[PDB]
Amino acid sequence: MAEMGSKGVTAGKIASNVQKKLTRAQEKVLQKLY
Image (tube, rainbow, N blue to C red):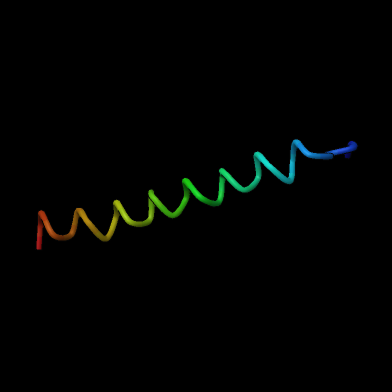
């Protein structure tokens, strides 16, 4: 554990955000195959 001030609350938002882009990639590749 630690302080996790504006570091975890901020950088944590980017992680979740980029995650969406990865999930979108998965659904998009299906367009190439299927």
